[PDB]
Structures are given as structure tokens and as C-alpha cells.
Image (tube, rainbow, N blue to C red):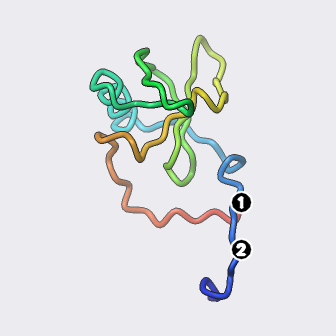
Amino acid sequence: MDRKLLHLLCSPDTRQPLSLLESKGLEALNKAIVSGTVQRADGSIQNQSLHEALITRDRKQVFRIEDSIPVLLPEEAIATIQIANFPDKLEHHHHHH
């Protein structure tokens, strides 16, 4: 354990194993959309609610799925830290990748 000596620590958060968003989380995104607090990477609000979505292992960001294609576009990525309805997972998220 050298966290304080590690003056340069960074993880591939943009290349960690993507998963499918839980239902209780999914409704939280849509709730936040209708609430008008879901701002995409650009900072603009999202109005189109979704039925499928991808979630980071850290549960920090969400990606959009449309038609059938997982939309991995940065501008289509939502930050859960902005989702005032997002339910906590009580897990210590650790990924060496």
C-alpha cells in the first residue's frame, strides 16, 4: 500500500469491462431525463428516454443503446454523479484494468 507515494495513478476507466444497466438504475436515468438533469458529455440535457443502457464497472458512467446498436459515443455517455435518482451499490469498485 503506497497510495501517498503513488504521485501518478491512472486507470483505463474508458476501457474497463462494460456491463448491462440494472433496472433500478435504468429507471433512475429515465426519471432524471424527465426531471431534466441528465446532461451528456457536451453539457446539454437528454430528452429521449431509453430501454437499454450500458454501465461502467465503477458505476460512474452510462452509455446509450439504440435500435440494437450499443452507442459508445462519448457525447451519448451519461454521468451517474449527475443522476439525483441513482441508487448506491455499496460495493468497493476496484479494477486493475
Q: Observer-nearest residue: 86 or 78?
A: 78
Rendering quarter of residue 19: top right
Q: From what the image shows, is residue 92 above or below residue 36? A: below
Q: Position of residue 72 (x, y in %)?
A: 66, 29
Image quarter of the N terminus: bottom right
Q: Amino acid at mark 1?
A: His
Q: Amino acid at mark 2?
A: Leu
Which residue is at 34% across, 43% downward? 86
Callout 1: SS? loop
Compared to residue 13, the image places residue 29 above or below, namely above
Coordinates of residue 10 in the picture (x, y in percent): 69, 65
Q: Position of residue 82 (x, y in %)?
A: 39, 42
Residue bearing the label numbered 2: 8
- Residue 87 falls left or right of residue 49: left
Q: Quadrant of the C terminus?
A: bottom right
Query: Residue 36 falls in which quadrant of the image?
Result: top left
Residue picked out by circle 1: 97
Question: Residue at position x 71%, y 55% from top?
Answer: 12
Q: Nearer the viewer, residue 51 or 73?
A: 73
Which tag, 1 or 2, sits closer to the chain's start? 2
Which residue lies at the image location 41% right of the left edge and 47% below the top edge? Answer: 81
Q: Position of residue 92 (x, y in %)?
A: 47, 67
Residue at mark 1 to residue at mark 2: CA–CA distance: 16 Å
Q: Residues within 10 Å of mark 2 (few under 14, many from 20)?
A: few
Tell me if mark 1 has few (under 14), some (14-19) or many (20+) residues whose alpha carbon lies within 10 angstroms of its own. Answer: few
The local secondary structure at tag 2 comes to: loop
